Image (cartoon, rainbow, N blue to C red; front, side, top):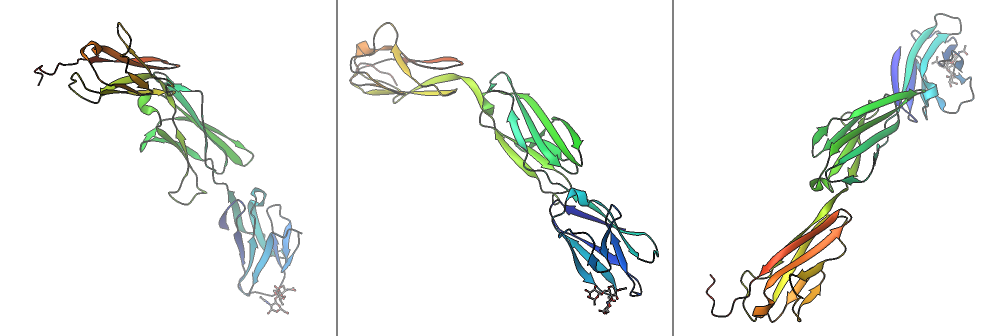
Length: 288
Ligand SMILES: *[C@@H]1O[C@H](CO[C@@H]2O[C@@H](C)[C@@H](O)[C@@H](O)[C@@H]2O)[C@@H](O[C@@H]2O[C@H](CO)[C@@H](O)[C@H](O)[C@H]2NC(C)=O)[C@H](O)[C@H]1NC(C)=O
């Protein structure tokens, strides 16, 4: 009895070996033990079954668009009841689709991200594996059979911080219906929110009276801060100051412009403020 295996909707071939062909009538039966081919003639009105070869050595039939209901034993016997012989058992497989990946809720630095991965239909039951940066994560899985096909789900949960924002997680599904070594994969991009940062970088290390200084405020955060605020301790920004987004330009600096300058930004997880100490040296000061 030949073990024959097809992917759902694919093509299988079933062959009856006959030995010293008498010329008598060959009955081929399906898994319900209903006559499917009477000698060379199809006995059931199913256009997916086609006689392919009736030679002195074998009778071969082809099945197109294989369905789960086609599974079971197929038989070949002489109408004279020489023997009830099973000549094949058909098994129909179902490969997983690319898995569906979801997240429980918005992940926030300091908290957890919780992901699920689901394959709704596979046969045999797909195996689900989680990867991050080539390294496998340990998840938790469950599945069940719904008729002849299995639904399988897996979940993983881990702490995140801002370094994980934008990181890629892979869920990978495998089963025997896929060619050896191959996989069905789904990528998921982490979105981790975090409180902002602010840092000032100045266009010069040493500032002299007469200089034009540019301060640049580098900001991070998720969500992205919408607005940079520039300010100064104790008193107002110099009259010539030009605060345009992330840059503060201080032209024509004079001694009285010295002081502490700040840039600040915010998102829904908090504020960040950077401070810059501005020293303005007269032309004769010895600094370096
Ligand atoms: C049952 O069928 C076999 C197979 O041949 C069938 O008939 C062929 C002529 C052709 O129409 C094919 O499509 C069929 O599969 C019969 O064996 C054949 O007998 C015929 C006699 O006309 C001759 O064509 C072939 O040489 C034979 N082929 C083989 C492989 O033996 C067989 O006689 C049929 N049996 C009965 C009881 O009717």
